[PDB]
Image: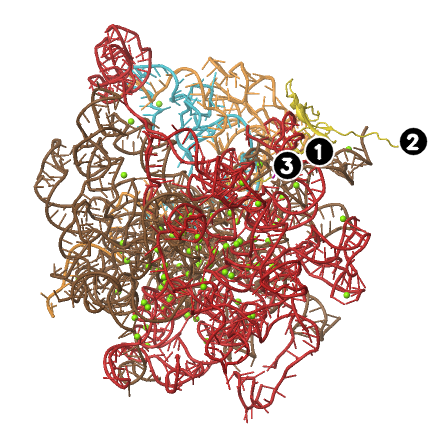
Chain colours: A yellow, B red, C brown, D cyan, E orange
Amino acid sequence: KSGGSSKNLGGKSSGRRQGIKKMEGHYVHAGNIIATQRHFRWHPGAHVGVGKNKCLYALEEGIVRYTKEVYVPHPRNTEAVDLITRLPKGAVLYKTFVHVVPAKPEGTFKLVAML
RNA sequence: GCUAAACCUAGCCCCAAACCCACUCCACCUUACUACCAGCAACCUUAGCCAAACCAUUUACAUAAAGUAUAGGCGAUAGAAAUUGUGGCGCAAUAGAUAUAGUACCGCAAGGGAAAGAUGAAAAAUUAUAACCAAGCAUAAUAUAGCAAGGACUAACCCCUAUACCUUCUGCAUAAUGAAUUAACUAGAAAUAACUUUGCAAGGAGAGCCAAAGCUAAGACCCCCGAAACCAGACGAGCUACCUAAGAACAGCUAAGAGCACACCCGUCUAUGUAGCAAAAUAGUGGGAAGAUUUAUAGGUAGAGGCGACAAACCUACCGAGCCUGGUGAUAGCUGGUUGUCCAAGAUAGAAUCUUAGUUCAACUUUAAAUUUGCCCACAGAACCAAAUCCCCUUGUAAAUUUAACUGUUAGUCCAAAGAGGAACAGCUCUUUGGACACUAGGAAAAAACCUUGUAGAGAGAGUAAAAAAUUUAACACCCAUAGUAGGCCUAAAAGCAGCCACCAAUUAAGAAAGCGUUCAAGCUCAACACCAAAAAUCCCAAACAUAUAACUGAACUCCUCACACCCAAUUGGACCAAUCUAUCACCCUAUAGAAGAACUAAUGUUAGUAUAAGUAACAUGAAAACAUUCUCCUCCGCAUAAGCCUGCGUCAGA
RNA sequence: GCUCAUAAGGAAAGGUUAAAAAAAGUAAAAGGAACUCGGCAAAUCUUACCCCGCCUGUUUACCAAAAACAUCACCUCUAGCAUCACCAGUAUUAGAGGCACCGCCUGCCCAGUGACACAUGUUUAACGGCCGCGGUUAACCGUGCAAAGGUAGCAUAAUCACUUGUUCCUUAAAUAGGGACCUGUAUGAAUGGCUCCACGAGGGUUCAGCUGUCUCUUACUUUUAACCAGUGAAAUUGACCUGCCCGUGAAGAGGCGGGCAUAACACAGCAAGACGAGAAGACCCUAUGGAGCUUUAAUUUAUUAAUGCAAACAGUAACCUGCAUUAAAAAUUUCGGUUGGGGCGACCUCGGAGCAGAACCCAACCUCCGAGCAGUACAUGCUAAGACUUCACCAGUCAAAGCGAACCUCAAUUGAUCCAAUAACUUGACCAACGGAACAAGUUACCCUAGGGAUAACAGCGCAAUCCUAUUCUAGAGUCCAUAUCAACAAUAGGGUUUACGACCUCGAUGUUGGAUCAGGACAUCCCGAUGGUGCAGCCGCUAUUAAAGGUUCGUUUGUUCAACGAUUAAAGUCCUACGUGAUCUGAGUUCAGACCGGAGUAAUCCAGGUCGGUUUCUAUCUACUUUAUUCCUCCCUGUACGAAAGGACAAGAGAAAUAAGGCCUACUUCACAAAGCGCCUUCCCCCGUAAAUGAUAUCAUCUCAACUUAGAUACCCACACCCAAGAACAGGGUU
RNA sequence: CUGGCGGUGCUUCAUAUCCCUCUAGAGGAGCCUGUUCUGUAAUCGAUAAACCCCGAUCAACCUCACCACCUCUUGCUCAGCCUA
RNA sequence: CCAUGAGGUGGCAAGAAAUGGGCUACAUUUUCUACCCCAGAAACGAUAGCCCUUAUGAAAUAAGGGUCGAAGGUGGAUUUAGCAGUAAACUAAGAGUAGAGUGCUUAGUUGAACAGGGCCCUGAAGCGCGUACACACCGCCCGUCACCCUCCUCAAGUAUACUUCAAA
Ligand SMILES: [Mg+2]
Ligand SMILES: [Mg+2]
Ligand SMILES: [Mg+2]
Ligand SMILES: [Mg+2]
Ligand SMILES: [Mg+2]
Ligand SMILES: [Mg+2]
Ligand SMILES: [Mg+2]
Ligand SMILES: [Mg+2]
Ligand SMILES: [Mg+2]
Ligand SMILES: [Mg+2]
Ligand SMILES: [Mg+2]
Ligand SMILES: [Mg+2]
Ligand SMILES: [Mg+2]
Ligand SMILES: [Mg+2]
Ligand SMILES: [Mg+2]
Ligand SMILES: [Mg+2]
Ligand SMILES: [Mg+2]
Ligand SMILES: [Mg+2]
Ligand SMILES: [Mg+2]
Ligand SMILES: [Mg+2]
Ligand SMILES: [Mg+2]
Ligand SMILES: [Mg+2]
Ligand SMILES: [Mg+2]
Ligand SMILES: [Mg+2]
Ligand SMILES: [Mg+2]
Ligand SMILES: [Mg+2]
Ligand SMILES: [Mg+2]
Ligand SMILES: [Mg+2]
Ligand SMILES: [Mg+2]
Ligand SMILES: [Mg+2]
Ligand SMILES: [Mg+2]
Ligand SMILES: [Mg+2]
Ligand SMILES: [Mg+2]
Ligand SMILES: [Mg+2]
Ligand SMILES: [Mg+2]
Ligand SMILES: [Mg+2]
Ligand SMILES: [Mg+2]
Ligand SMILES: [Mg+2]
Ligand SMILES: [Mg+2]
Ligand SMILES: [Mg+2]
Ligand SMILES: [Mg+2]
Ligand SMILES: [Mg+2]
Ligand SMILES: [Mg+2]
Ligand SMILES: [Mg+2]
Ligand SMILES: [Mg+2]
Ligand SMILES: [Mg+2]
Ligand SMILES: [Mg+2]
Ligand SMILES: [Mg+2]
Ligand SMILES: [Mg+2]
Ligand SMILES: [Mg+2]
Ligand SMILES: [Mg+2]
Ligand SMILES: [Mg+2]
Ligand SMILES: [Mg+2]
Ligand SMILES: [Mg+2]
Ligand SMILES: [Mg+2]
Ligand SMILES: [Mg+2]
Ligand SMILES: [Mg+2]
Ligand SMILES: [Mg+2]
Ligand SMILES: [Mg+2]
Ligand SMILES: [Mg+2]
Ligand SMILES: [Mg+2]
Ligand SMILES: [Mg+2]
Ligand SMILES: [Mg+2]
Ligand SMILES: [Mg+2]
Ligand SMILES: [Mg+2]
Ligand SMILES: [Mg+2]
Ligand SMILES: [Mg+2]
Ligand SMILES: [Mg+2]
Ligand SMILES: [Mg+2]
Ligand SMILES: [Mg+2]
Ligand SMILES: [Mg+2]
Ligand SMILES: [Mg+2]
Ligand SMILES: [Mg+2]
Ligand SMILES: [Mg+2]
Ligand SMILES: [Mg+2]
Ligand SMILES: [Mg+2]
Ligand SMILES: [Mg+2]
Ligand SMILES: [Mg+2]
Ligand SMILES: [Mg+2]
Ligand SMILES: [Mg+2]
């Protein structure tokens, strides 16, 4: 027995727990993490921030909603521009975005005093 | 009825209170119980087990301050002061002091250690109580068969049923340990904190301690036996190893640490013995037997040591270092056990750990309480390199979150599918989804895991779920033969089959040839025409019928009369209760509260008697006789003494 | 100290019979070691060899008595001296060591350790070592390195498999014994190499004699056994009203599912089972439980002696005490985890790919890819709503804003407490055994203890990777000729007999192989019986089926079944029986303590290396048991049938020999009023596998898984008391 | 006994000789010149005094009698023979 | 014996590998110029190609005429002859090549040292010693392992033949 005992070590990693934390229809508050995962899964949509680990987190109190909108990234990403140019005429990427439909308003004009 | 069973009084533990004893007569440090004569003696840090999962520094010897400061491989732990101020809710011969006594017994020695008895006013009462109560036997031996029991039965057996208990482990009669019963003893002491009920309240408690509803007081919770092994000093050279002083022994024969051979020293081998003669024996063959020889007496060498012709052998039957005392009831992830009745809830994804036989967290489970949403939920929502899964309103329901507690689980096995390595094998090792087993019920033969089925009782009632293996392949249409010829290439040769070509066509109507056999041709058929699966070793294993009408039998499942808390491992929450003492009327034996040395089918548990092999193994005493005496055999044995014992086969009376 | 057998000293037989088994003695018809690993009890009394040890002597009282231990002889080192020994001694004297007398010898090396301050070197008779690559079965060439590179010598060793060596004998067989070869690659010199005078309870062979060890055992006495009288234990027991076969069953059933059986107890033997009975298996494994031994493992020098300093006095311009070093040997401790049993090999932290395919999720002694970092600012600044969170915790990740300036990329890429530096921001780990004791090794076959078949060596159990047996298409051979016969590439069925594989009860015990008596069963049949084919002119042969009623040798070696060989008969078959049977036996060794040979190891110890020897218990309780024809040789068949000659048979009858069983002492022996064999008599029935009349499905033909015919139980029996050929008692026969 | 030989002894000579002194050149590169011969169809004889600036006083062919290609029996020679 | 011969075109004349010799020049009077012996400076070598192939010719090796006008670096033992027209320098004709240079025969000019001492190396002559040598030191030669091989001695246990028996 040599060269085939257990030289292929290293595979002893636990689960990273990276998925969806607030499914669609849930009343998420401002600041809660919506999901965490590697590689841009759900691109940022309306009222959805992005941290450093390519994660998402709600910014306003509302219900989470997912749609399929066209993808038009920033010209900075030369790789994205190249991939787009490599597509034919009638071609669309259609990525998965995330939205947060706001419920409450930003404020209300209340009566202070009668002068 | 033999053997048995009980008596309870002597004495023990606690403190409550004082501080105790001690030479008539001789004798006692030499060899202790010895009338008598010329020689140093004293003061010493205790170690160690154990806990930090090892272990070195470390670990204990009135109240409050305060378990604070402080010290501490700053971790396990240790831890001050100033200030303060004359009886038993005991024991009653396996209990109580070990005690009738520190008695024999082990013993040369330190050292360890038990029981004696049972009526009373008269035992200078003759004369016995009332038999009854466990274990072993008699009155009284068995009469097909099989966990010693049930339904029964008019009856014992005969009929059907069911695989001893506890512990472990996923799984049990298993052939895994425990066990002969009986009587006695024998194994959960409490903690910061938490729950319930009393009393007062922003205060209570009989200074001190706690206060954004708190404190006080009570009730309720933390097992036993079991090593190897260390420390300090005693006791041990009377046997073994060595040394010292003075003594003893060694026939004879042949002839010098010479040879054979008495006594004598040790035992290389056989046989018997193996609970024997002996916790190391009996005969010869064995080596020596004027010398490194054996031994009588006394003294010296004692464990971190002594000794040692090294056997790492011996030092009082067991020496890789003898026993005792006090630390040690040492420790121990480990074997074993952990006592009365009944009801209810009650099976776990994983991680860390000098770690996978152990511990913590998480998760499962239990108790009391405040809150409201817990599960299948429907459109929809949830990725570029198949069964599926998450959220999910109405809808079935009544379950879920949290607070405060704390023990218990955290080694699993099998089945259907995805698999992973192995041989697309293993009652093979490990995951994912579901079920079962650890929990009873009816079957597949005896089955854990397979099919059906759960809320617990009776009735000599009714209706159902699962439920009984089937099946025998081999013929065959079997009438019948001219020729252009030996076509051509190679083949001396294959002409019809060593090899290739086209494969025509005359027979009236069909192969330049589909097989067989020829070196080669010779011969025999055919295409077509004319009726035509079993075998392995103790002996195969339920009797058994193909022919009376499809439906029966078949549970702890459902129903019928009553009332229902009365079928889980570990754990948890509750209702009762045999015995004793205490305070209460009782008083032919019971109630309210206070306590547990409070409740035995087991811990190769201890004490006492008794079954079991078992009347089996072991065993002796030479013969006749007038018990005067005589006869047969053996002898390396016998005489006195140093070592050692203390009256230990003579008489008198009874055993 | 005495005569050691006599003037001393004692009674081996409680009484009857002599069942079975064992032991102590007497003899034995032919052999004298041929059963046996061994000449191991009893008798002769004895001849020649090898290894080792100088010979005597001692060792493990209590399993190993030696090939070990010690020295008369040689050699190494230390000591210049007197009052307790060493010493009332003095260098030829003593102390500490290596080897083994005597003879031939002790060849080389201080790189490394130790001892000598020897002015830098000595010491190997101290610890230890004496080499490799290509060549006309090798000298000598080309060389590399150090200390030399095994010199002499001995040889298949007590010397790692090769090993049962080669080689010639010793016998009928020789892994037993011995004459020579280095090739012993790991022999080889006072860790001593070789011969030899005497010797060995040391370990292995052998020539002429020897015995019951066996061939084949028998008769007698005693011990001893049974009954009648007495007393009188222990190991052990859950209760037993206790059978057998098939299958299951925590995996070998007297109590389970189905069948066979079963009147009651008692003695006389039994050791197959009740995984039988005595010891918390001694072999394997766990223990942050121990102890012995060894140092260059982690620590302290308590103690001894010498060193430098201090006080301590004499000199000038000599004893104690305290502080650190050195050698000795002393004082405490440990020897981490995984391993489909333990060591060995490998691993110990983290990220990704498939298992885990569509929220998360899960296993690495399953197959892979990577990292203890890498590049520019230093607003990588100070604050703070809400969340994710490697399935716990400790540890990690995103973030609206608020103040201050604007007009980071990557995937793991790491480090907790205490402690230390630091005036103070801040920093300190290959703690990788990476959730991390502040630093600790090797062995135990001299081991102890608490436990484990959670976890091993033998079994049982399940698989069938390996093998064997049969069949299927023929590939290929077999002179034409696949299928008389052999048989590739594959598939279908049976095996658990070999090697493993899994550890499911059996480590508070299942005693391990051969060899002895005894054998039970199965046929994949070696032979005796019957058939078909054949490369069958006959025997000798080959193949396929039935038949297990029977038989299945004598010996030489190595402990080994297996393993080689000599002669037989027709054959010297396989397999299971817990590698059948140790409560029937055996010890040869396999698990032990001591020693030797070569090696590993600085040392203790070990080679799963080789041998010298190594206490084998049981008093029976239960179940169960304890009395009924086989072959070979010979004679008429004889030289027959068969050819080309050699060669050479079928059946039947008869004589004799053995096998196993049933009997006897009158001849022969052991011997005597008996019994036994070596001596003598008897032993008898076919076995299902084939070949044939007669005809249909299938008017042919045709043996019948269509109808019908051929080779196709006899034996023993069932009316008190004395002796016995009957018997342990009981029972039986005779008693004119 | 003759001779050879001697790092063999003694004595006498060497007059560019053997040294004690002195001259131009080889021991530095290119053309010509040779040799053993790898190219080849290609003489190569001597290959240390006795052989190479020897046929060389010269290798476009003539030197070259060596083969790629053709030649002949009277072979200009009563041949060539440079084939040993 | 119908060539192993020679005759008709072609060729070898570059160095696998080793190398002597003739010329070019390795520098300060090298290379340049005047006085026909009145001085200095940079401190110089087409060595071969290409055509006319010169010298000829069927066909061209140092070339007379058009392209290298530079680059090499007096070297260590040893070596050649030279006692004076010698060593060393400065110029021409030509045997022979049809064909020629830097070679060779002849014809010319300038012109050293020491010209003295010894066998230490070498050669010769006279006396003499030794000789295992004689195709004569390039000799004989001694001892290391042996095939076709010729023999012997020792050797523990073995097999065969043989003397002694009775002279007791
Ligand atoms: Mg992975
Ligand atoms: Mg403790
Ligand atoms: Mg501790
Ligand atoms: Mg005070
Ligand atoms: Mg008492
Ligand atoms: Mg008491
Ligand atoms: Mg009774
Ligand atoms: Mg019963
Ligand atoms: Mg229990
Ligand atoms: Mg238990
Ligand atoms: Mg288990
Ligand atoms: Mg049992
Ligand atoms: Mg409150
Ligand atoms: Mg003594
Ligand atoms: Mg002794
Ligand atoms: Mg012996
Ligand atoms: Mg015994
Ligand atoms: Mg002796
Ligand atoms: Mg003697
Ligand atoms: Mg004597
Ligand atoms: Mg002790
Ligand atoms: Mg304890
Ligand atoms: Mg542990
Ligand atoms: Mg147990
Ligand atoms: Mg109890
Ligand atoms: Mg329940
Ligand atoms: Mg750790
Ligand atoms: Mg398993
Ligand atoms: Mg269960
Ligand atoms: Mg019900
Ligand atoms: Mg009791
Ligand atoms: Mg027991
Ligand atoms: Mg008990
Ligand atoms: Mg008995
Ligand atoms: Mg007697
Ligand atoms: Mg008797
Ligand atoms: Mg005889
Ligand atoms: Mg005999
Ligand atoms: Mg035998
Ligand atoms: Mg034998
Ligand atoms: Mg023998
Ligand atoms: Mg003899
Ligand atoms: Mg000796
Ligand atoms: Mg012993
Ligand atoms: Mg002995
Ligand atoms: Mg000695
Ligand atoms: Mg001596
Ligand atoms: Mg030596
Ligand atoms: Mg060997
Ligand atoms: Mg008896
Ligand atoms: Mg009796
Ligand atoms: Mg017992
Ligand atoms: Mg069974
Ligand atoms: Mg049983
Ligand atoms: Mg047992
Ligand atoms: Mg045990
Ligand atoms: Mg301990
Ligand atoms: Mg300990
Ligand atoms: Mg392990
Ligand atoms: Mg978490
Ligand atoms: Mg902002
Ligand atoms: Mg971690
Ligand atoms: Mg660490
Ligand atoms: Mg540690
Ligand atoms: Mg040993
Ligand atoms: Mg096994
Ligand atoms: Mg063929
Ligand atoms: Mg197991
Ligand atoms: Mg075991
Ligand atoms: Mg055990
Ligand atoms: Mg047992
Ligand atoms: Mg058969
Ligand atoms: Mg066996
Ligand atoms: Mg047995
Ligand atoms: Mg020893
Ligand atoms: Mg030796
Ligand atoms: Mg026995
Ligand atoms: Mg009996
Ligand atoms: Mg009985
Ligand atoms: Mg010629």
Spatial CA distance of label 2 from label 3 is 59 Å
Are labels 3 and 1 assigned to the same chain?
yes
Amino acid type of the residue that numbered disc 3 sits on in the rendered structure: Arg
Which stretch appears magenta?
Answer: A14-18
Q: Would you call the spot at circle 1 few (<14 residues within 10 Å), some (14-19), or many (20 or more)?
A: few
Observer-side mark, 2 or 3, equals: 2
Q: Would you call the spot at circle 3 few (<14 residues within 10 Å), some (14-19), or many (20 or more)?
A: few
Across and down, in percent, residue B619 comes to 33, 71
The disc at residue A17 is: 3
The disc at residue A51 is: 1
Instruction: Work out whether C386 lies above or below E36.
Output: below
Spatial CA distance of label 1 from label 2 is 48 Å
Task: Tell which of B162 and C64 is nearer to you.
Answer: B162
The residue at which mark 2 appears reads as A115
Report the label total: 3
Spatial CA distance of label 3 from label 1 is 17 Å
Q: In the rendered structure, which disc, 2 or 3, sits on the residue that comes first in sequence?
A: 3
Chain ID for label 1? Answer: A
Do the numbered discs 2 and 3 sit on residues whose CB atoms are within 8 Å?
no
- Indicate yes or no whether the magenta region holds residue A76: no
Observer-side mark, 3 or 1, equals: 3
Observer-side mark, 1 or 2, equals: 2
Q: In the rendered structure, which disc, 1 or 2, sits on the residue that comes first in sequence?
A: 1
Q: Would you call the spot at circle 2 few (<14 residues within 10 Å), some (14-19), or many (20 or more)?
A: few
